[PDB]
Image (cartoon, rainbow over all chains, first blue to last red):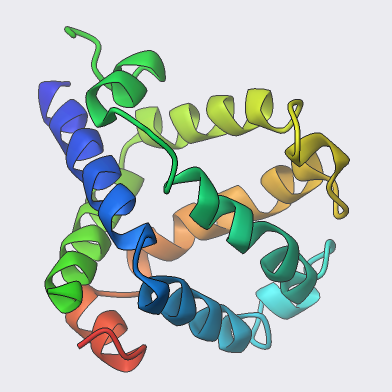
Length: 82
Length: 77
């Protein structure tokens, strides 16, 4: 729906802004330190902490790149009417 | 400023995680994205992380946290 399209555009727009802030990455990191030590996260294979160490810097980097929110949401099927 | 951005993103994410189309779009994007550089050379394997963690994160944002509490608790407010 158009509402899901607008939600996507807003999400991506805020993520491009927030990923530039060092505090946002720090908060996500600290929160995941604690979440990796509670159920079910602690039982998971690949290990939660290893995933957080390898992938969070790259996920943060992806959203710091030049992304047009309207284009990204449109390309991945979240705007069926355009 | 950051506190406002956080609450907005957390709020929009719970909403979006209740849609099948959203989970499906994330899934398709990461499947193709796991086959290009630098993702394809990463250990633990990108496809394995997606397969094991995406349903759990989705289920996490659907019913386990709210914005004021998350942002305030993790130092953004």
